[PDB]
Image (cartoon, rainbow over the protein chains, first blue to last red):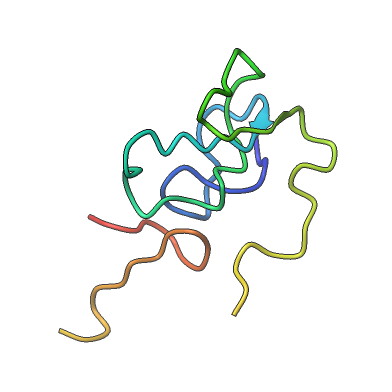
Length: 71
Length: 18
């Protein structure tokens, strides 16, 4: 838990934070206001890929960054 | 209707909608 980004709202860090994976499955016109390339907060590389732009990683330099926003 | 509603998301504040 506490990877980097968040599911929909901020502050929290999703319920399942086993592996941090930058999954971007826009599928079709995405859903809500999207996210910062869904940095992660899910399971490990289970197959993913194919269309969905994801970069799975078990932390260790996945989130260590200055900030999310950037005026 | 002014500073009542606000869409957070991404990073800044808590719960977005209601």
